[PDB]
Image 1 (tube, rainbow, N blue to C red):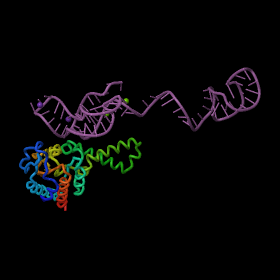
Image 2 (image 1 turned 45 degrees about the vertical axis):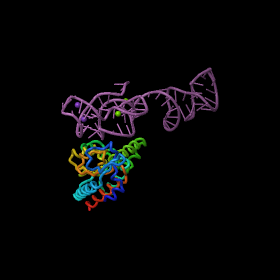
Image 3 (image 1 turned 180 degrees about the horizontal axis):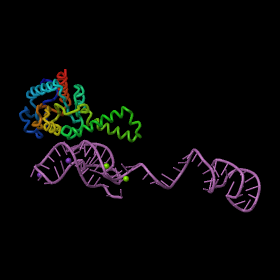
Length: 222
RNA sequence: UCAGCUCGUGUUGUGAAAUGUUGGGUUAAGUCCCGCAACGAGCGCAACCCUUAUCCUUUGUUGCCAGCGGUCCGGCCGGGAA
Ligand SMILES: [K+]
Ligand SMILES: [K+]
Ligand SMILES: [Mg+2]
Ligand SMILES: [Mg+2]
């Protein structure tokens, strides 16, 4: 709803100087040298994206949430876990999708290390070796924790800030994976299949998007 | 004995190529961490080997002599295993 979005601060945009001219249709206007996104445009476009996401969920298609920004990192994890969907909330590895075959090997290493930790193999290691393994496991977990159970290419991508996650979008476009993304005034919307014009900086705005997308997929799954 | 030299897949470039391997620190070291369109891997680095420095255990002659006994004063002898 528009009332919730204005409360969330979805309408707030970046400063006019950093705008991308392709975003002009979505922008309502500028106040205090800050672009204001037209919520009237956002609400129908958000609804259309949610409807498609619901359909993909009904088909049992895997959904990947990307939110590398630290502010939204935890929220992206929680929303994906809530809907039992895969996520990436730390730096996106270039070639995660395009070079999935190579990236899979790291996933296999992560799960092996996890089992070894549970096994107590680390105890057999001479402390230092265990520490190295532990450090490796932590790094692998942060990067590949969300996609460890994905076991293939995601059927759809939901992205926060298209500009920040340009690599991920470019990979998705290459592999013909549909992209759903929140595009702020500064960002370019050409890559995204389904564009949602909203603030991506604000956690409150981010949570609103994530809550809705998690809910719609969950209904699709049911 | 210098810390270099490369590859697969991905990505960028019409292309030769590039990236990875650069960057911020750090190291004897492409050593390590962090960052990062790269993600991984191999040969090198290091370690694994030999010798040297300390200690313990076992063994005690052809090596040893602290404590005993005796001396031809030489562990020399009976001994002892320190
Ligand atoms: K050129
Ligand atoms: K290459
Ligand atoms: Mg090395
Ligand atoms: Mg060596």
